[PDB]
């Protein structure tokens, strides 16, 4: 889950506070590659 | 080998066979290799109808395995709301700490079972309760980034 990746502990500061991955990055499910996008009769679509 | 058949029946969810083995007088606190009673297995796999039958024939509700985990730990961890109530109503230790200092609230908070967390708190579940790492059920909610859970524990 994105929630599990978000709370990955990058480091703990000297004052006790801790830097999670969600503090330095946005966590979402997204394509391996965003180059390829298809439309069927001008309507958002995928295909094989 | 009668209390051993009860363990297998309790896990399988065979409501009838448990009552049949109970009539013949099988050990209700018959523990397996890892120290799980029939009540443990029923709580984990979520056989509420069996949990009621076991507790009615005096199944040790505060029975703990070889790592100090009780049926309430399992019930609260795997989101078995009905079983958590039935356990607590039959005098289950809500502040029960395992070998790691983890309580049913810690497990309920971790998996984000918001309903069960409220039921534990209702029966006097210690919110300030820490584990071996000095982490409360609220420290879990902030790290998990749970909005709904964090508001309940403050």
Image: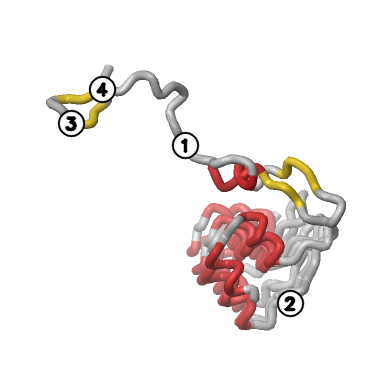
Q: Nearer the viewer, residue B73 or A8?
A: A8
Label 1 chain ID:
A
Which of the colour schemes (rainbow, by chain, secondary structure, one colour) is used?
Answer: secondary structure
Of the pair B52 and B136, the residue shown nearer to us: B136
Looking at the image, residue B66 lies above or below residue B62: above
- Compared with B82, B41 (above or below) is above
Instruction: Say which quadrant the N terminus of chain B sits in.
Output: bottom right
Mark before the other along the chain sequence, 4 or 3: 4
- Report how far apart the C-alphas of labels 3 and 2 lie in the structure: 55 Å
Q: Which residue in the protein does label 1 denote?
A: A29
Residue B31 position within the rendered picture, expressed as x and y whole percent measured from the top left: 74, 58
Give the residue pinned by disc 4.
A38
Query: Do tags 1 and 2 sit on the same chain?
Result: no
Label 4 to label 1: alpha-carbon separation:
19 Å
Q: Nearer the viewer, mark 1 or mark 2?
A: 1
Mark 2 crowd level (few <14, some 14–19, many ≥20, 10 Å Cα): some
Residue B29: x %, y % from top left = 72, 66
Q: What chain does mark 2 sit on?
A: B
Secondary element type, mark 3? strand
Q: Which residue is mark 2?
A: B126
Is residue B103 left or right of A23 when viewed as pictured?
A: right
Q: CA distance from mark 1 to mark 2?
A: 37 Å
SS of the residue at dot 4? strand
Q: Which residue is mark 3?
A: A43
Same chain for marks 3 and 1? Answer: yes
Q: Residue furthest top?
A: A48
Q: Quadrant of residue B141?
A: bottom right
- Residue B126, located in which quarter of the rendered image? bottom right
Alpha-carbon span between mark 2 and mark 4: 55 Å
């Amino acid at each position: 889950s994105t929630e599990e990746f978000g709370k990955i502990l990058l480091k703990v500061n000297q004052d006790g506070s801790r830097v999670l991955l969600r503090d330095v990055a946005k966590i979402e499910l997204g394509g391996e590659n965003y180059d390829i996008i298809a439309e069927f009769n001008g309507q958002p679509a995928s295909g094989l | 080998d009668l209390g051993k058949k009860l363990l297998e029946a309790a896990r399988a969810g065979r409501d009838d066979e448990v009552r049949i083995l109970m009539a013949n007088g099988a050990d209700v606190n018959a523990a397996d290799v890892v120290g799980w009673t029939p009540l443990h297995l029923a709580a984990y796999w979520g056989h509420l109808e069996i949990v009621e039958v076991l507790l009615k024939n005096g199944a040790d509700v505060n029975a703990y395995d070889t790592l100090g985990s009780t049926p309430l730990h399992l019930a609260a961890h795997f989101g078995h709301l009905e079983i958590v109530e039935v356990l607590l109503k039959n005098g289950a230790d809500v502040n029960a700490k395992d070998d790691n200092g983890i309580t049913p609230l810690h497990l309920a908070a971790n998996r984000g079972h918001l309903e069960i967390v409220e039921v534990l708190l209702k029966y006097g579940a210690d919110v300030n309760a820490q584990d071996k790492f000095g982490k409360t059920a609220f420290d879990i909610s902030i790290n998990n980034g749970n909005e709904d859970l964090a508001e309940i524990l403050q």
